[PDB]
Image (spheres, coloured by chain):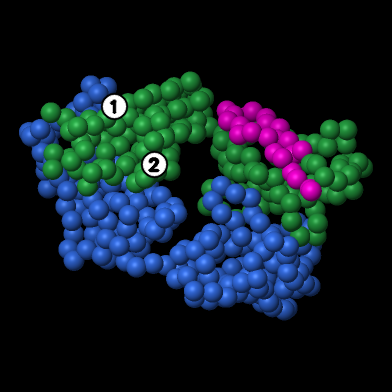
Chain colours: A green, B blue
Amino acid sequence: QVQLQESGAEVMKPGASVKISCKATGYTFSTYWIEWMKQRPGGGLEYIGEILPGSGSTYYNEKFKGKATFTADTSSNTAYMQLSSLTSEDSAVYYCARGDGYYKYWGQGTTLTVSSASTKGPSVFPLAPSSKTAALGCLVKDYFPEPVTVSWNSGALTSGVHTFPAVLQSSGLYSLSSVVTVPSSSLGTQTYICNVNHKPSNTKVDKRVEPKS
Amino acid sequence: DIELTQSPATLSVTPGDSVSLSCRASQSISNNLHWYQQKSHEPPRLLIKYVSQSVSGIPSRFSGSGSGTDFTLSINSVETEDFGMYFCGQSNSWPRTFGGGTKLEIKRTVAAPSVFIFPPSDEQLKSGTASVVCLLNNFYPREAKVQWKVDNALQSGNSQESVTEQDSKDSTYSLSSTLTLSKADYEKHKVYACEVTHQGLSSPVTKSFNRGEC
């Protein structure tokens, strides 16, 4: 059962270096190539290069000679790609695949964000239902980096939820909304909490969303 | 290198219909042409290998064809699970290259949006900023015009839109339009309006509030 397992998301300041791992399992590590691809948001796949673990032979797409550096360790069945002198152009999802002629077995993907911004948690503001089916929600504003999660009433409310993709603002900070449609009659007699969590700053916020008086 | 060119870039299909996506190569690549499907936040998944040969675990409705520099992926009777991005990939030479992709959307009855407008909270105001929010909910197709009017003045580059992927229940879209103004500017005007134009509306729907009224 061949399986490739990549490492977690990474957020670095420009000019830093990052190393992404690809842990193979299910076969002799040193007999198949490990190939690396870069995919930018809403874009195609781009070949970085590839390594043969045991020999350590390497090929590099000429575009990435400066940027990427492949290493491997046979002992721990793990391949590495090191991206150096980072810039925002390196913001992308990085994949590793086993060389099978075709790419049958892929790693799950690694998100690399490169940005000036610094870790900041969001402010959460009510989207308050109208003065006259209703909609309410939470505005999750000015945070860094991705991601934030939003549940409603600790997950007892999921029907009719929409949590938009974040938009990156001029400030380098992200902003996001989550909305839910509910019965009109319920708005006076009930409680609606949006449970926001931004792990990179330990922001856990449970915001009451009520119609204004 | 080898350049791979896919067309169309976009296709809406209603389930049961059949589609042929095209992939053209800049020079010959033998039969080392493969097809991949990729869903959101997922690694691509091998669909057809070696121009036309079956791949383990892939539904039979997918099939690939072609020769020389002209290849096709066919989906006999598309299903609702087949939304996503479709790439061809060559492996005849290094570097490996991929086409631009075709986004397969699922086509569906036209659904007008429900429109809702949200004034900025008081909390956010005290901190210097007003985010006014317009929600267009559960509509299809994707094209929609959202027009902000502040005291009937038509707003320009002071808003950002954000759209969901096709809903997993009814294949609709939802989008948010966020007007962002300074507290000062927001408090220079009374009547904040969001005007939505969409195929399923006989005329534009306007949602508004007045800062003078709770």
Asked if residue B103 lies in the magenta stretch, the reply is no
B91 shown above or below B180: below
Tell me the element at label 2: loop
Q: Position of residue A199 (x, y in %)?
A: 50, 25
Label 1 secondary element: strand
Q: How far apart are labels 2 and 1 at the CA level?
A: 16 Å
Expressed as whole percent of the image width and height from the top left, the position of residue A41 reads 53, 48
Badge 2 and badge 1 both on one subunit: yes
Q: Residue furthest left?
A: B212
Q: Chain of mark 2?
A: A
The crowding category of the residue bearing disc 1, from other C-alpha atoms within 10 Å (few below 14, some 14 to 19, many at least 20), is some
Residue type at mark 1: give it: Arg
Label 2 Cα crowd, 10 Å radius (few <14 / some 14-19 / many 20+): few
Residue that label 1 marks: A208
**In the image, is B154 to the left or to the right of A58?**
left
Image height of A152 relative to A102, above or below: above
Q: Label 2: which residue?
A: A158
What x and y, as percent, mark residue B193?
17, 46
Q: Which of the two residues, A128 or B57, is positioned nearer the viewer here?
A: B57
Q: Residue at x 10, y 32 (%)?
A: B214
**Over which residues does the magenta segment extend?**
A1-23
Query: In terms of depth relative to the viewer, which is nearer, B180 or B63?
Result: B63
Taking the spot 63% from the left edge, 74% from the top edge, the residue there is B72
